[PDB]
Image (tube, rainbow over all chains, first blue to last red):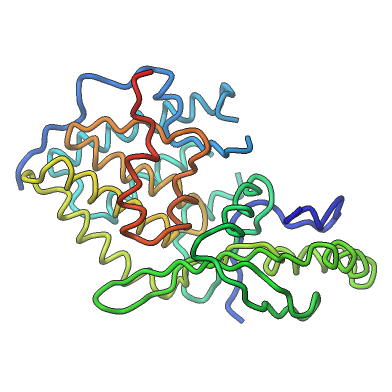
Length: 23
Length: 291
């Protein structure tokens, strides 16, 4: 279990490349 | 320049054509009607671009990347802009290691070049993580590329993720996990794209010369593939474009590259290795078996 920590997480991240403004 | 042979008359068997550009995760779509068609479409557009390359009709790697983008775009839709735009230096690129990237988690944890660092998070706190740091060397200078992170303190995660959901709210939590998910890939800084695109143009220029041994040609193609994919130049569809460009260059020389073996996702295999390493294994990632 390396990624099963977010079991049934309604806020899980979507599986694809996302872009954000550099902080 | 000097016209190249162009795509070979002897084509791949139809079942292979339908596997071109596929994402065959070792843990899992490539058998579906829409994917077969999508893959056969890529195979065909690659040959078309290849014909052009052989006639000197595509003189820059940027031009070739443009053809790849047009193809991928015709296969699309609000996400259009993302598949058509390059990554600007005012942004970061992050891919959370969630379905369908689960197989990656283990690849990072057991990687020979992985190490343990502490990843501080203003929500989960400091986390122990297995980290793979892809770097490149161009003109004598290191240039860090993609960085993979996989947290090991699982127990703590599932419990802590819980409290946060209710404390901050699902909406806010997702906004955070989307960029700072405990297990994720932080992609090559867009600021390096300018210098990398120029390099891709030199590789392209070389792969367009008519006097190269097959071996040299394959290595040049594997290199180009590695750089294009690891750089992940566009906001979306970089893997598809990188593979298109690589195959097209090959097709221009009369080489019919077979689909990547099942379990081998080309762009991920690239992000997980150094340049020479990937160049030496490229051939083995391709399914070139008769039976």
